[PDB]
View 1: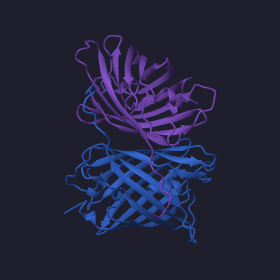
View 2 (view 1 turned 180 degrees about the vertical axis):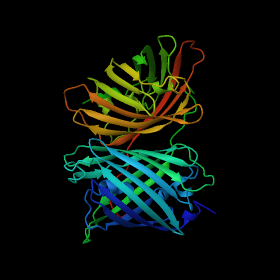
View 3 (view 1 turned 90 degrees about the vertical axis):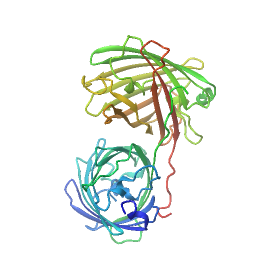
Amino acid sequence: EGGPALFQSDMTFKIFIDGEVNGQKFTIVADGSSKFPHGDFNVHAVCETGKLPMSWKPICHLIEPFFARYPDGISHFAQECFPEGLSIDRTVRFENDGTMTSHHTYELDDTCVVSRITVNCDGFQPDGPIMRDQLVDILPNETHMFPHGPNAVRQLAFIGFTTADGGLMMGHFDSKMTFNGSRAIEIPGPHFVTIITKQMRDTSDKRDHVCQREVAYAHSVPRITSAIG
Amino acid sequence: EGGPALFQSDMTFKIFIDGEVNGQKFTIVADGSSKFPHGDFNVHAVCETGKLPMSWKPICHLIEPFFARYPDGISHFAQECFPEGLSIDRTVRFENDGTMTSHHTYELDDTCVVSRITVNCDGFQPDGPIMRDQLVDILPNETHMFPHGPNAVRQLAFIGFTTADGGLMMGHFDSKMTFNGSRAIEIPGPHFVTIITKQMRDTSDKRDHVCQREVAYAHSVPRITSAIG
Protein backbone atom coordinates (compact mmCIF):
# COMPACT_ATOMS: atom_id res chain seq x y z
CA GLU A 1 0.00 0.00 0.00
CA GLY A 2 -0.96 2.56 1.12
CA GLY A 3 -1.89 5.57 3.31
CA PRO A 4 -1.44 4.68 7.00
CA ALA A 5 1.02 2.14 5.52
CA LEU A 6 3.19 5.07 4.56
CA PHE A 7 3.25 6.27 8.18
CA GLN A 8 4.69 3.19 9.85
CA SER A 9 8.27 4.52 9.71
CA ASP A 10 9.67 7.33 11.81
CA MET A 11 9.08 10.69 10.16
CA THR A 12 10.34 14.19 9.48
CA PHE A 13 8.19 17.04 8.38
CA LYS A 14 8.49 20.53 6.94
CA ILE A 15 6.23 23.51 7.45
CA PHE A 16 6.37 26.64 5.30
CA ILE A 17 3.98 29.21 6.80
CA ASP A 18 3.41 32.48 4.93
CA GLY A 19 1.36 34.69 7.22
CA GLU A 20 0.44 38.26 8.11
CA VAL A 21 -1.55 39.94 10.90
CA ASN A 22 -3.23 43.33 10.39
CA GLY A 23 -0.59 44.06 7.72
CA GLN A 24 2.88 42.87 8.65
CA LYS A 25 3.65 40.02 6.27
CA PHE A 26 6.00 37.41 7.78
CA THR A 27 7.43 34.00 7.00
CA ILE A 28 7.82 31.02 9.30
CA VAL A 29 9.69 27.82 8.46
CA ALA A 30 9.58 24.81 10.77
CA ASP A 31 10.67 21.24 10.65
CA GLY A 32 9.68 18.14 12.40
CA SER A 33 10.17 14.99 14.32
CA SER A 34 7.60 12.32 14.95
CA LYS A 35 8.53 8.81 15.87
CA PHE A 36 6.25 5.91 15.10
CA PRO A 37 3.69 5.34 16.50
CA HIS A 38 3.49 9.13 16.69
CA GLY A 39 1.05 10.84 19.02
CA ASP A 40 3.94 12.64 20.67
CA PHE A 41 5.98 15.07 18.64
CA ASN A 42 7.81 18.39 18.93
CA VAL A 43 8.33 21.22 16.51
CA HIS A 44 11.10 23.67 15.92
CA ALA A 45 9.88 26.66 14.05
CA VAL A 46 11.84 29.71 13.13
CA CYS A 47 10.47 33.13 12.29
CA GLU A 48 12.34 33.90 9.02
CA THR A 49 11.34 37.58 8.93
CA GLY A 50 13.28 37.79 12.19
CA LYS A 51 10.75 38.73 14.81
CA LEU A 52 7.15 37.53 14.91
CA PRO A 53 4.70 40.54 15.11
CA MET A 54 2.37 38.77 17.53
CA SER A 55 2.21 35.97 20.09
CA TRP A 56 3.39 32.47 19.17
CA LYS A 57 0.49 31.03 21.15
CA PRO A 58 -2.21 31.20 18.41
CA ILE A 59 0.39 29.72 16.09
CA CYS A 60 0.35 26.36 17.81
CA HIS A 61 -2.31 24.79 15.57
CA LEU A 62 -0.54 26.08 12.48
CA ILE A 63 2.68 24.24 13.43
CA GLU A 64 0.13 17.96 11.84
CA PRO A 65 -3.06 15.87 12.19
CA PHE A 66 -1.49 12.84 10.48
CA PHE A 67 0.82 12.57 13.47
CA ALA A 68 -2.07 12.09 15.97
CA ARG A 69 -2.15 8.59 17.33
CA TYR A 70 -5.28 6.72 16.23
CA PRO A 71 -6.60 3.46 17.72
CA ASP A 72 -7.42 0.71 15.24
CA GLY A 73 -11.15 0.93 14.65
CA ILE A 74 -11.17 4.67 14.11
CA SER A 75 -10.08 5.36 10.51
CA HIS A 76 -7.14 7.82 10.36
CA PHE A 77 -8.42 10.32 7.81
CA ALA A 78 -5.48 12.67 7.89
CA GLN A 79 -3.18 9.74 7.15
CA GLU A 80 -5.41 8.14 4.49
CA CYS A 81 -5.32 11.39 2.52
CA PHE A 82 -1.87 10.19 1.37
CA PRO A 83 -0.09 10.15 -0.96
CA GLU A 84 -2.49 12.43 -2.81
CA GLY A 85 -2.30 14.66 0.25
CA LEU A 86 -4.90 16.95 1.78
CA SER A 87 -5.93 20.55 2.15
CA ILE A 88 -7.33 22.36 5.17
CA ASP A 89 -9.44 25.44 5.62
CA ARG A 90 -9.67 26.79 9.19
CA THR A 91 -11.11 29.81 10.97
CA VAL A 92 -10.43 30.54 14.60
CA ARG A 93 -12.65 33.28 16.05
CA PHE A 94 -11.35 34.74 19.33
CA GLU A 95 -14.11 36.51 21.24
CA ASN A 96 -13.77 40.29 21.52
CA ASP A 97 -10.73 39.96 19.30
CA GLY A 98 -9.42 38.79 15.93
CA THR A 99 -9.79 35.81 13.59
CA MET A 100 -7.11 33.68 12.09
CA THR A 101 -7.98 32.16 8.74
CA SER A 102 -5.58 29.62 7.43
CA HIS A 103 -5.37 27.62 4.26
CA HIS A 104 -2.98 24.67 4.38
CA THR A 105 -1.97 22.17 1.71
CA TYR A 106 0.14 19.05 2.28
CA GLU A 107 2.44 16.85 0.26
CA LEU A 108 4.23 13.67 1.14
CA ASP A 109 7.99 13.52 0.37
CA ASP A 110 8.40 9.75 0.51
CA THR A 111 8.98 9.97 4.33
CA CYS A 112 8.72 13.71 4.82
CA VAL A 113 5.60 15.92 4.98
CA VAL A 114 5.67 19.27 3.32
CA SER A 115 3.20 21.72 4.75
CA ARG A 116 2.61 25.06 3.07
CA ILE A 117 0.31 27.55 4.77
CA THR A 118 -1.31 30.91 4.36
CA VAL A 119 -2.72 32.64 7.38
CA ASN A 120 -4.35 36.05 7.67
CA CYS A 121 -5.07 37.56 11.11
CA ASP A 122 -7.48 40.48 11.13
CA GLY A 123 -9.78 42.59 13.33
CA PHE A 124 -7.37 41.77 16.15
CA GLN A 125 -6.89 44.00 19.16
CA PRO A 126 -3.41 45.61 18.99
CA ASP A 127 -3.81 46.51 22.64
CA GLY A 128 -5.29 43.06 23.46
CA PRO A 129 -3.78 39.85 24.93
CA ILE A 130 -2.43 38.40 21.58
CA MET A 131 -0.55 41.49 20.39
CA ARG A 132 0.42 42.77 23.90
CA ASP A 133 1.50 39.13 24.33
CA GLN A 134 -0.53 38.65 27.49
CA LEU A 135 -1.18 34.97 26.61
CA VAL A 136 -0.05 32.85 29.55
CA ASP A 137 -0.85 29.20 28.74
CA ILE A 138 -2.77 27.00 26.23
CA LEU A 139 -5.48 24.82 27.78
CA PRO A 140 -5.55 21.22 26.57
CA ASN A 141 -8.72 20.12 24.79
CA GLU A 142 -10.89 17.46 23.31
CA THR A 143 -11.39 18.51 19.69
CA HIS A 144 -14.47 17.10 17.99
CA MET A 145 -14.14 15.39 14.56
CA PHE A 146 -17.23 14.82 12.37
CA PRO A 147 -17.72 13.24 8.88
CA HIS A 148 -18.08 16.11 6.43
CA GLY A 149 -19.67 14.79 3.20
CA PRO A 150 -17.94 12.20 0.97
CA ASN A 151 -14.36 13.38 1.02
CA ALA A 152 -13.69 15.36 4.13
CA VAL A 153 -13.88 15.81 7.83
CA ARG A 154 -14.53 18.66 10.12
CA GLN A 155 -12.69 19.47 13.38
CA LEU A 156 -14.41 21.70 15.86
CA ALA A 157 -12.54 22.85 18.98
CA PHE A 158 -12.72 25.45 21.80
CA ILE A 159 -9.24 26.74 22.33
CA GLY A 160 -8.46 28.10 25.76
CA PHE A 161 -5.74 30.72 26.37
CA THR A 162 -5.05 32.14 29.85
CA THR A 163 -4.75 35.96 30.09
CA ALA A 164 -2.10 37.99 31.93
CA ASP A 165 -4.53 38.83 34.69
CA GLY A 166 -5.67 35.22 35.02
CA GLY A 167 -8.78 35.47 32.89
CA LEU A 168 -9.61 33.50 29.74
CA MET A 169 -9.52 34.29 26.00
CA MET A 170 -11.73 31.74 24.21
CA GLY A 171 -11.09 30.83 20.54
CA HIS A 172 -13.60 29.09 18.20
CA PHE A 173 -11.73 26.72 15.90
CA ASP A 174 -13.55 25.44 12.77
CA SER A 175 -11.38 23.44 10.49
CA LYS A 176 -12.14 21.34 7.40
CA MET A 177 -9.72 18.81 6.05
CA THR A 178 -10.46 17.77 2.44
CA PHE A 179 -8.87 14.98 0.47
CA ASN A 180 -7.13 16.24 -2.70
CA GLY A 181 -7.59 13.02 -4.71
CA SER A 182 -10.32 11.46 -6.78
CA ARG A 183 -10.37 7.88 -5.47
CA ALA A 184 -12.63 6.79 -2.66
CA ILE A 185 -11.55 7.27 0.97
CA GLU A 186 -13.24 6.24 4.18
CA ILE A 187 -14.68 9.02 6.27
CA PRO A 188 -14.43 8.02 9.94
CA GLY A 189 -17.62 8.40 12.11
CA PRO A 190 -17.77 11.11 14.84
CA HIS A 191 -14.82 10.92 17.28
CA PHE A 192 -12.43 13.08 19.30
CA VAL A 193 -8.78 13.94 19.26
CA THR A 194 -7.21 14.99 22.46
CA ILE A 195 -4.63 17.65 22.05
CA ILE A 196 -2.15 18.73 24.75
CA THR A 197 0.34 21.41 23.92
CA LYS A 198 3.35 23.09 25.47
CA GLN A 199 5.09 26.11 23.97
CA MET A 200 8.30 28.11 24.60
CA ARG A 201 11.05 30.19 22.96
CA ASP A 202 14.14 27.96 22.81
CA THR A 203 16.30 30.30 24.93
CA SER A 204 19.41 29.54 22.83
CA ASP A 205 18.56 31.27 19.52
CA LYS A 206 19.58 34.71 18.18
CA ARG A 207 16.48 34.82 15.93
CA ASP A 208 12.83 34.85 17.15
CA HIS A 209 11.45 31.31 17.23
CA VAL A 210 10.12 28.57 19.56
CA CYS A 211 10.13 24.91 20.43
CA GLN A 212 6.76 23.23 20.79
CA ARG A 213 5.45 19.93 22.13
CA GLU A 214 2.06 18.32 21.37
CA VAL A 215 0.43 15.12 22.61
CA ALA A 216 -2.57 14.28 20.46
CA TYR A 217 -4.61 11.11 20.20
CA ALA A 218 -7.99 10.04 18.93
CA HIS A 219 -10.59 8.28 20.97
CA SER A 220 -14.26 7.63 20.79
CA VAL A 221 -16.62 7.51 23.78
CA PRO A 222 -19.13 5.03 25.31
CA ARG A 223 -22.31 3.97 23.56
CA ILE A 224 -25.49 3.45 25.48
CA THR A 225 -27.27 0.22 24.76
CA SER A 226 -30.79 1.12 26.01
CA ALA A 227 -32.54 3.98 27.91
CA ILE A 228 -33.78 1.57 30.65
CA GLY A 229 -31.70 -1.65 30.66
CA GLU B 1 -18.81 24.60 52.10
CA GLY B 2 -20.69 21.28 52.54
CA GLY B 3 -22.57 21.00 49.22
CA PRO B 4 -20.81 17.84 47.95
CA ALA B 5 -21.63 16.30 51.35
CA LEU B 6 -25.33 16.55 50.43
CA PHE B 7 -24.89 14.72 47.09
CA GLN B 8 -23.39 11.71 48.88
CA SER B 9 -26.93 10.24 49.17
CA ASP B 10 -29.25 9.05 46.41
CA MET B 11 -31.33 11.91 45.15
CA THR B 12 -34.30 12.59 42.90
CA PHE B 13 -35.16 15.46 40.67
CA LYS B 14 -38.14 17.28 39.25
CA ILE B 15 -38.11 19.57 36.21
CA PHE B 16 -40.63 22.14 34.92
CA ILE B 17 -39.99 23.54 31.51
CA ASP B 18 -42.02 26.47 30.09
CA GLY B 19 -41.30 26.53 26.41
CA GLU B 20 -42.05 28.28 23.23
CA VAL B 21 -41.19 27.46 19.63
CA ASN B 22 -42.08 29.63 16.62
CA GLY B 23 -44.66 31.31 18.83
CA GLN B 24 -46.33 28.07 19.96
CA LYS B 25 -46.24 27.44 23.71
CA PHE B 26 -45.37 24.12 25.17
CA THR B 27 -44.87 22.64 28.58
CA ILE B 28 -42.76 19.74 29.70
CA VAL B 29 -42.58 18.14 33.16
CA ALA B 30 -39.96 15.62 34.18
CA ASP B 31 -38.76 13.50 37.07
CA GLY B 32 -36.04 11.00 37.66
CA SER B 33 -33.45 9.56 39.97
CA SER B 34 -29.65 9.41 40.39
CA LYS B 35 -28.21 6.85 42.89
CA PHE B 36 -24.75 7.43 44.31
CA PRO B 37 -22.25 7.45 42.86
CA HIS B 38 -24.42 9.18 40.20
CA GLY B 39 -23.16 9.82 36.61
CA ASP B 40 -25.63 7.48 35.06
CA PHE B 41 -29.06 8.87 35.73
CA ASN B 42 -32.43 8.62 33.98
CA VAL B 43 -35.37 10.95 33.54
CA HIS B 44 -38.91 10.45 32.52
CA ALA B 45 -40.16 13.49 30.46
CA VAL B 46 -43.73 14.28 29.53
CA CYS B 47 -45.12 17.08 27.35
CA GLU B 48 -48.03 18.49 29.43
CA THR B 49 -49.57 20.29 26.44
CA GLY B 50 -50.52 17.16 24.55
CA LYS B 51 -48.18 16.75 21.60
CA LEU B 52 -44.69 18.35 21.47
CA PRO B 53 -44.36 20.46 18.31
CA MET B 54 -40.67 19.79 17.72
CA SER B 55 -38.22 16.86 17.88
CA TRP B 56 -37.60 15.68 21.46
CA LYS B 57 -33.89 15.28 20.67
CA PRO B 58 -32.87 18.96 21.11
CA ILE B 59 -34.72 18.97 24.49
CA CYS B 60 -32.03 16.57 25.82
CA HIS B 61 -29.74 19.10 27.60
CA LEU B 62 -32.86 20.67 29.18
CA ILE B 63 -33.95 17.59 31.04
CA GLU B 64 -28.58 17.97 35.91
CA PRO B 65 -24.91 18.81 36.04
CA PHE B 66 -24.80 17.96 39.76
CA PHE B 67 -25.45 14.39 38.75
CA ALA B 68 -22.29 14.19 36.72
CA ARG B 69 -19.87 11.94 38.55
CA TYR B 70 -16.74 13.88 39.25
CA PRO B 71 -13.42 12.30 40.43
CA ASP B 72 -11.38 13.79 43.32
CA GLY B 73 -9.02 16.63 42.34
CA ILE B 74 -11.63 18.52 40.31
CA SER B 75 -14.01 20.75 42.22
CA HIS B 76 -17.56 19.64 41.38
CA PHE B 77 -18.94 23.21 41.17
CA ALA B 78 -22.63 22.47 40.55
CA GLN B 79 -22.50 20.49 43.73
CA GLU B 80 -20.74 23.08 45.85
CA CYS B 81 -23.62 25.29 44.74
CA PHE B 82 -25.99 24.08 47.41
CA PRO B 83 -27.62 24.47 49.74
CA GLU B 84 -28.13 27.90 48.25
CA GLY B 85 -28.43 26.84 44.64
CA LEU B 86 -27.54 27.77 41.13
CA SER B 87 -28.90 29.14 37.91
CA ILE B 88 -27.97 28.60 34.25
CA ASP B 89 -28.24 30.92 31.28
CA ARG B 90 -27.82 28.73 28.17
CA THR B 91 -27.91 29.40 24.39
CA VAL B 92 -27.77 26.74 21.70
CA ARG B 93 -27.33 28.17 18.22
CA PHE B 94 -28.19 25.48 15.56
CA GLU B 95 -26.33 25.72 12.27
CA ASN B 96 -28.85 27.08 9.71
CA ASP B 97 -31.65 26.71 12.09
CA GLY B 98 -32.84 28.58 15.10
CA THR B 99 -31.59 29.33 18.58
CA MET B 100 -32.69 27.81 21.87
CA THR B 101 -32.37 30.28 24.75
CA SER B 102 -32.92 28.96 28.28
CA HIS B 103 -32.77 30.20 31.86
CA HIS B 104 -32.67 27.54 34.58
CA THR B 105 -32.91 27.77 38.38
CA TYR B 106 -32.07 24.92 40.67
CA GLU B 107 -33.36 24.41 44.21
CA LEU B 108 -32.74 21.61 46.62
CA ASP B 109 -35.68 20.19 48.60
CA ASP B 110 -34.05 17.74 51.00
CA THR B 111 -32.82 15.12 48.54
CA CYS B 112 -34.78 16.49 45.57
CA VAL B 113 -33.49 19.01 43.10
CA VAL B 114 -36.35 20.93 41.64
CA SER B 115 -35.60 22.51 38.33
CA ARG B 116 -37.48 25.35 36.71
CA ILE B 117 -36.64 26.33 33.14
CA THR B 118 -38.02 28.75 30.65
CA VAL B 119 -36.83 28.17 27.07
CA ASN B 120 -37.57 30.14 23.93
CA CYS B 121 -36.82 28.56 20.57
CA ASP B 122 -36.74 31.07 17.77
CA GLY B 123 -36.08 31.24 14.10
CA PHE B 124 -36.47 27.50 13.73
CA GLN B 125 -36.90 26.22 10.14
CA PRO B 126 -40.49 24.82 9.94
CA ASP B 127 -39.46 22.36 7.23
CA GLY B 128 -36.15 21.65 9.03
CA PRO B 129 -35.17 18.35 10.69
CA ILE B 130 -35.99 19.70 14.16
CA MET B 131 -39.55 20.85 13.46
CA ARG B 132 -40.13 17.79 11.20
CA ASP B 133 -38.99 15.33 13.87
CA GLN B 134 -36.26 13.88 11.63
CA LEU B 135 -33.50 13.77 14.25
CA VAL B 136 -32.44 10.26 14.81
CA ASP B 137 -29.97 10.27 17.68
CA ILE B 138 -27.71 12.42 19.77
CA LEU B 139 -23.90 12.35 19.41
CA PRO B 140 -21.87 11.91 22.62
CA ASN B 141 -19.86 14.94 23.39
CA GLU B 142 -16.98 16.33 25.39
CA THR B 143 -18.22 19.53 26.85
CA HIS B 144 -15.43 21.90 27.95
CA MET B 145 -15.94 23.37 31.47
CA PHE B 146 -13.99 26.56 32.25
CA PRO B 147 -13.91 28.59 35.49
CA HIS B 148 -15.64 31.94 34.99
CA GLY B 149 -15.32 35.00 37.25
CA PRO B 150 -15.60 34.58 41.02
CA ASN B 151 -19.15 33.12 40.96
CA ALA B 152 -19.56 31.09 37.78
CA VAL B 153 -18.38 28.37 35.40
CA ARG B 154 -18.84 28.32 31.62
CA GLN B 155 -19.78 25.17 29.72
CA LEU B 156 -19.17 24.91 25.95
CA ALA B 157 -19.96 22.04 23.63
CA PHE B 158 -20.68 20.80 20.13
CA ILE B 159 -23.99 19.05 20.38
CA GLY B 160 -24.67 17.19 17.11
CA PHE B 161 -27.71 15.14 16.06
CA THR B 162 -27.90 12.70 13.12
CA THR B 163 -30.70 13.51 10.79
CA ALA B 164 -32.88 10.93 9.00
CA ASP B 165 -30.99 11.19 5.68
CA GLY B 166 -27.91 10.43 7.79
CA GLY B 167 -26.57 14.02 7.65
CA LEU B 168 -25.72 16.14 10.75
CA MET B 169 -27.49 18.92 12.60
CA MET B 170 -24.89 20.75 14.73
CA GLY B 171 -25.60 22.97 17.79
CA HIS B 172 -23.15 25.52 19.26
CA PHE B 173 -23.82 25.21 23.03
CA ASP B 174 -22.82 27.95 25.46
CA SER B 175 -23.86 27.83 29.05
CA LYS B 176 -23.19 29.85 32.13
CA MET B 177 -23.81 28.21 35.54
CA THR B 178 -24.03 30.78 38.39
CA PHE B 179 -23.75 30.43 42.13
CA ASN B 180 -26.75 32.02 43.71
CA GLY B 181 -25.00 32.27 47.08
CA SER B 182 -23.07 35.23 48.47
CA ARG B 183 -20.22 33.27 50.07
CA ALA B 184 -17.17 32.34 48.03
CA ILE B 185 -17.12 28.96 46.42
CA GLU B 186 -14.26 27.09 44.79
CA ILE B 187 -13.96 27.73 41.06
CA PRO B 188 -12.63 24.48 39.51
CA GLY B 189 -10.03 24.50 36.82
CA PRO B 190 -10.56 23.94 33.09
CA HIS B 191 -11.79 20.41 32.55
CA PHE B 192 -14.35 18.40 30.61
CA VAL B 193 -17.45 16.47 31.14
CA THR B 194 -18.22 13.64 28.72
CA ILE B 195 -21.96 13.22 28.08
CA ILE B 196 -23.67 10.31 26.41
CA THR B 197 -27.38 10.49 25.87
CA LYS B 198 -30.03 8.21 24.66
CA GLN B 199 -33.82 8.65 24.34
CA MET B 200 -36.50 5.96 24.05
CA ARG B 201 -40.27 5.70 24.22
CA ASP B 202 -41.65 3.77 27.20
CA THR B 203 -44.53 1.99 25.41
CA SER B 204 -46.58 1.62 28.62
CA ASP B 205 -46.90 5.44 29.13
CA LYS B 206 -49.54 6.52 26.56
CA ARG B 207 -48.62 10.25 26.94
CA ASP B 208 -46.21 12.17 24.73
CA HIS B 209 -43.02 11.37 26.62
CA VAL B 210 -39.40 10.31 26.48
CA CYS B 211 -37.24 8.30 28.80
CA GLN B 212 -33.73 9.57 28.62
CA ARG B 213 -30.65 7.96 30.02
CA GLU B 214 -27.56 10.00 30.57
CA VAL B 215 -23.96 8.99 31.34
CA ALA B 216 -21.89 11.93 32.43
CA TYR B 217 -18.42 12.04 33.90
CA ALA B 218 -15.86 14.70 34.33
CA HIS B 219 -12.19 14.17 33.55
CA SER B 220 -9.26 16.46 33.07
CA VAL B 221 -6.38 16.12 30.69
CA PRO B 222 -2.80 15.82 31.98
CA ARG B 223 -0.79 18.98 31.08
CA ILE B 224 2.68 18.21 29.55
CA THR B 225 5.55 19.91 31.44
CA SER B 226 8.70 19.19 29.51
CA ALA B 227 8.69 20.69 26.03
CA ILE B 228 10.91 17.67 25.51
CA GLY B 229 9.65 14.30 26.80
